[PDB]
Image (cartoon, rainbow, N blue to C red; front, top):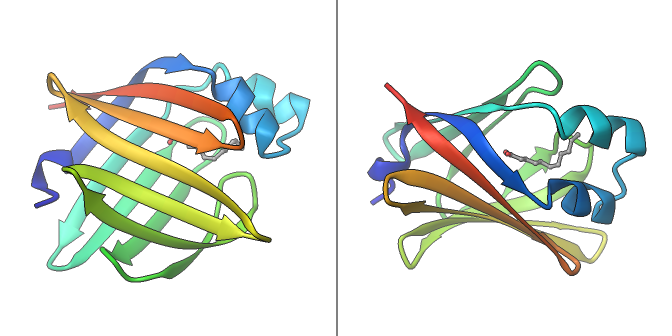
Length: 133
Ligand SMILES: CCCCCCCCCCC(=O)O
């Protein structure tokens, strides 16, 4: 069900990421570096367990999870959140909850590109990833 998401992906477009980061309270110097960074995202499975790596010259993260099972996560901007990832309409939907706040990280495949939509508050960011061979 998740298999078309698997592989190595590189950032090739970003819209409103500064808005999203600012909404989360990320400081200006971090936003400045992140606005110029192009991460590589690696999505792998082993049975029921997905691992999602995000690599860059600035921040690195890695999470492992089972779809539909809550997990603790510490985000790239150091939020300690309760997370769940599911498939919904063919999209990989990652919901993070902390302190009564929520953010969603929604991934969908359009014409072979991975579109990541990040929503927090009113901020909506769209980042496009292309597959590496
Ligand atoms: C410290 C920089 C901001 C991190 C905000 C939360 C994670 C964003 C992930 C974006 C992406 O995977 O393209």
